[PDB]
Length: 278
Ligand SMILES: C[N+](C)(C)CCO
Image (cartoon, rainbow, N blue to C red; front, side, top):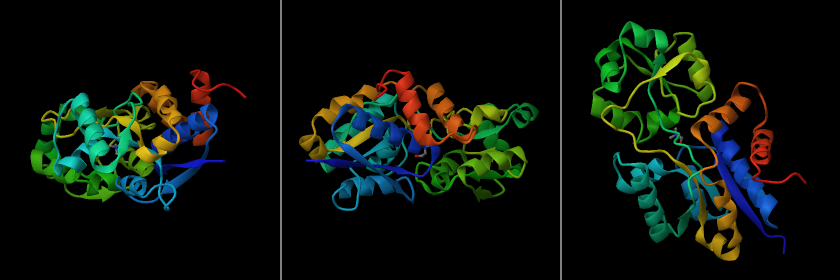
């Protein structure tokens, strides 16, 4: 029959790596072939694409983050434990959209606010509240996702009364260079970022708990599951298979060592026994 499915990703290192892992698992364990589609746009493009579907210029599968789905359902930022976010998005996406959340990959790739270790020492910074008290001295460099999202800087700034001198919208790798060069003093480091542990940076504590959990999980259209039921068990072979530290190392293989993400994804799966060498 030569059935195919479309796995989507937006264009950032982690997104492409885990989208490739999903594609590799499908091709290794089923007779399906995978179209890998890269979407330009923000944190909602894949959601609209999966509502369209791989037959109608959209996608069938992608890896979403629980807290993003949660804040989208609620219409305002909230905090909850990982189970609260996951169970809520799973039930709501099943009822409202016939989209099935599969099991979490294992890591929480949350937004953070991060500063240079030297700045944190010179002002004894530990928490977001500490940082807010001096924010009028500082420049924030942040991803477009962070500066535009309701779960991003808008709500955070309201809750903590952040008063940064200004914000600079920056590509993902650019913001690490910018904080290194002191063009900015704070960035929205993401917890799994490959460059993070390699730049002498301090992740500050979200002491008022503004951010939701951001656990990555594959999600799939129900009608694709209906046509190809094996996909459920196949994709759940990834359940809890990627820790925060493992994801960081894969991201660094791409962003720091220059390996291509397809190779990084496939080699990780082979080394962990999740696919076999052909
Ligand atoms: C994963 N983040 C929450 C850090 C943003 C991208 O969706």
